Image 1 (cartoon, rainbow, N blue to C red):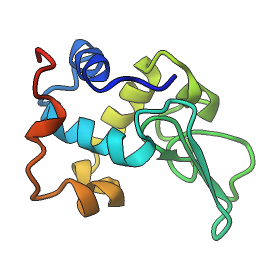
Image 2 (cartoon, rainbow, N blue to C red):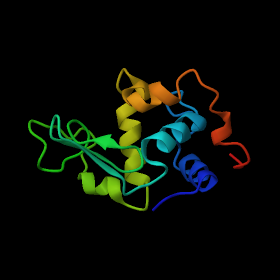
Image 3 (spheres, rainbow, N blue to C red):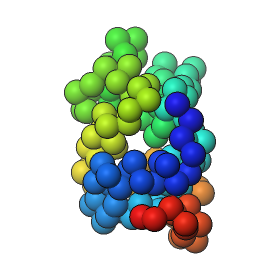
Length: 130
């Protein structure tokens, strides 16, 4: 599923993402936007370390989900990476929450640092009723 901007903002808010661990909905929107263009079936294989990024938040298999083919990987979200490719984003959100409970917080995603950190991200939620 490719979410439309406001549809996604409301979906994330309903799932309890607004201000989760001090992270605003606009930041999560900026992250999803830059990671996958709001696409839940997006995947990126990293030939360098044999890991793959999954879903709307492009969560990596080395530490967050199990795909059975990433060397010495762990599954901190205790999910099959398949769960991160569903149209329903419940599991991807549960896992993103797990990611940010770690010290790095939203900084875990390099794309967030590049295109969201210290930037005006208001535009992502404007007019969405969130």
